[PDB]
Image (cartoon, rainbow, N blue to C red):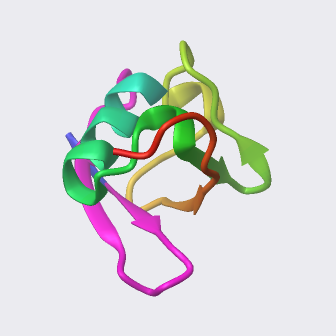
């Protein structure tokens, strides 16, 4: 396993324990548990790249202590 971080514009950030082989779906599911944001309302970014469902962390060269950036974009229903 390895630690990664998810940073938001409020400064209230998340630490996750992940594997390089984990998918973006996995990560977004974790963010949903921590923040209550459905995956389709999460715009997750690593170094300017929008992270897509069906890709792994490894595909984006996300590594030990990498920081991802979370932007919320509402569409569809809010919980």
| x and y percentages locating residue 5 in the rendered image | 38, 63
Identify the residue at the far right of this view.
Answer: 48
Q: Is residue 5 magenta?
A: yes
Residue at left 39%, top 49%? Answer: 37
| x and y percentages locating residue 13 in the rendered image | 36, 75
- Please state if 55 lies on the left or on the right of 11 as rendered: right
Residue at left 43%, top 62%? Answer: 6
Residue nearest the observer in this picture, 13 or 61: 13
Q: Is residue 54 above or below residue 10?
A: above
Q: Is residue 8 magenta?
A: yes
How many numbered marks appear? 0
Residue at left 39%, top 54%? Answer: 64
Quarter that holds the N terminus: top left
Residue at left 56%, top 20%? Answer: 53
Q: Is residue 14 above or below residue 46?
A: below
Identify the residue at the far top of this view.
Answer: 54
Q: Which residues are magenta?
A: 4-22
| Residue 34, image quadrant | bottom left
Identify the residue at the far front of this view.
Answer: 77
């Amino acid at each position: 396993g390895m630690p990664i971080f998810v940073k938001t514009l409020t400064g209230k950030n998340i630490t996750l324990e992940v594997e390089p082989s984990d998918t973006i779906e996995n990560v977004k599911a974790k963010i949903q548990d921590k923040e209550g944001i459905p995956p389709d309302q999460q715009r997750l970014i690593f170094t300017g790249k929008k992270l897509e469902d069906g890709r792994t962390l490894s595909d984006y060269n996300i590594k030990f202590a990498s920081t991802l950036h979370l932007v919320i974009r509402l569409r569809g229903a809010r919980p």
